[PDB]
Image (tube, coloured by chain):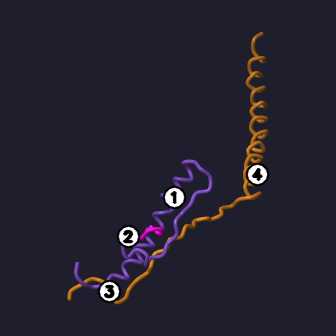
Chain colours: A orange, B purple
Amino acid sequence: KQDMPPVGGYGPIDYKRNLPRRGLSGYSMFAVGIGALLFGYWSMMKWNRERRRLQIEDFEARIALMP
Amino acid sequence: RKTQPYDVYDQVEFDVPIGSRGDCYDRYLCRVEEMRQSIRIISQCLNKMPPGEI
């Protein structure tokens, strides 16, 4: 008279299938990308242009000597 | 399993997954989907066991 099945206490667990979490898609991407990339080239032309100014100063000390 | 009997096996309910096209990726997906359907036939089996002999 000592046998298994309980009178109660059950679930069940699902048979389902779901993890579609979105996700920042669909014109949200391709907009943060271009907005990041244009910040890069804007951070250029303030350094590459400025280094060309110091470049001419480096040639300047050459030319003020050599006679 | 549901065109012939074995046992007391008629008394469970479940569906038999099918494939659409005829390749490996859609005979792969039976094996993923049958494992979800085998959980249903286990959870339906814990409720039904009669005490008795073996």
- The answer to if B3 sits in the magenta stretch is yes
Q: Which residues are magenta?
A: B1-6
Q: Nearer the viewer, residue A43 or A58?
A: A43
- Mark whose residue sits in front, 1 or 2: 2
Residue kind at label 4, given as amino acid type: Gly
Q: Which residue is mark 1?
A: B30
Q: Cα distance, mark 2 to mark 3?
A: 26 Å
Task: Classify 10 Å Cα crowding around label 3: few (below 14), some (14-19), many (20 and above).
Answer: few
Identity of the residue furthest to the top in this view: A67
Q: Cα distance, mark 4 to mark 1?
A: 44 Å
Identity of the residue furthest to the left in this view: A1
Q: Which residue is mark 4?
A: A35
- On the picture, is B39 further left or further right than A57? left
- Mark whose residue sits in front, 4 or 1: 1
- Mark whose residue sits in front, 2 or 3: 2
To which chain does the residue with label 3 belong?
A: A
**Could you say whether the residue bearing mark 3 is in a helix, strand or loop?**
loop
**Image point (52%, 66%), residue name:** B16
- The answer to if B21 sits in the magenta stretch is no
Q: Which residue is mark 3?
A: A6
**Quarter of image, res B46:** bottom left
Q: Is residue A3 above or below residue A56?
A: below
- Mark whose residue sits in front, 4 or 3: 3
**Marks 4/2 same chain:** no
Residue kind at label 3, given as amino acid type: Pro
**Marks 2/3 same chain:** no
Task: Classify 10 Å Cα crowding around label 4: few (below 14), some (14-19), many (20 and above).
Answer: few
**Quarter of image, res A54:** top right
Q: Position of residue A12 (x, y in %)?
A: 45, 78
Q: Which residue is mark 2?
A: B6
